[PDB]
Image (cartoon, rainbow, N blue to C red; front, side, top):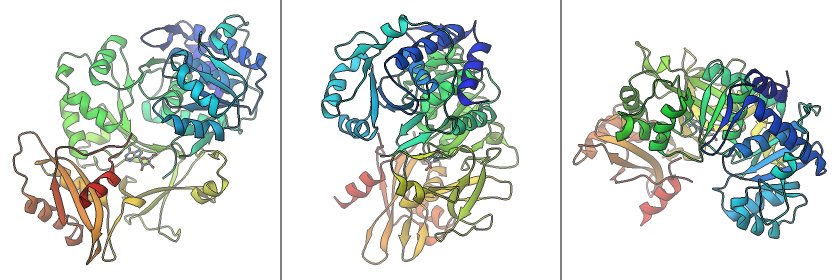
Length: 499
Ligand SMILES: Nc1ncnc2c1ncn2[C@@H]1O[C@H](CO)[C@@H](O)[C@H]1O
């Protein structure tokens, strides 16, 4: 239909229902559409035309979703900066963006000043009253809400998400965005949803909000994940979905307030983005008490690639918690060797994917794009193996593989064996220098609750008799905690091992 057409049709289908809900503001579908139309006119009145870059700096307010959609309705290129990014990383993105405008949240004017000092930008605009540039919400306030039709090229990029790559802005056009929408309906089920987005509107949260609106639903916004707030919100706002990082799942399931929370409105807790720990997902199932969990494997480059359904989490005759599920309709998966050759089902190699959800490409990085997408196939930089039912099992990121005297030890697979043991809650496996074998296998393991001394020889034996001898951790370190990224922090583990 056209992506922005899909979004607007959803909002019209929900004209009298709630569409954008935060702690501070609640808009109906019709109200949301009006704000979009008038914000779009305000932006066009500032001189913005199709293909103009619009860089933003905001949190997850209603104003932010409105802005994101309005920018794209014009056919401009939305480039959202995450607040969490370092100021210097922000400047770099801003410099690279060829920005025709910079739109910032008033709250954040200090940092906006730093950035614009580094990278002077025309059309500085604020989401409300603020020191720098003009007040976009004021300007939108005073335009007509007469509809603005999308007339730009469905194929030209309207959004740039920062944090692809295995820095990197990932360009997305309406075409690939609509395909992502269609896939989300397969994963999340038919709309309307009441979808708790606590992920940045700057990128993935913003996409999920778009899809929610497009399928006729309500976006329930939070700035970030805090388990007590989320448990309360699910009940108070009657959410059908909340998209989680795997660790968030475990925090919900283990929280003391879970008993008192009302989860009855949930249809799903879709999760992914980082490797799950199967045994911890198994505990979460039990604690939640019904098949809510849906495992989602995707990337900014690839869109949605596979999903494991809620019912496949509890399939009677299989155990699939170490799988990321099966291909989305329309998605082809090939598992390839180092030379690019397709491997028979069952073999480990690089996960490569072809679908209409593929990104347009990396913003201004043509060499890397041609390296990453070859003959229409995304090379994910993940390693894995399919089975005869079509389930995909990720065994490593290519960069994490540990080479022990010419043998390949897949760190995530070893981790799953360790965490599978009842004594082990969490594990991280990394390679360290070895005089004899070049690399040796190092594992850090966090004991489970009610576990005393880990039997390290038991753990080595389990790995040995599941994967084979070379997969065994030579070095096995009991730790209190596994360091994290802003994924588990494998470089940090590698470093702390020397000392
Ligand atoms: N559900 C998931 N399970 C494991 N790793 C994932 C999942 N979703 C995303 N990833 C990882 O993060 C990357 C996305 O930027 C993937 O290519 C993959 O390595």
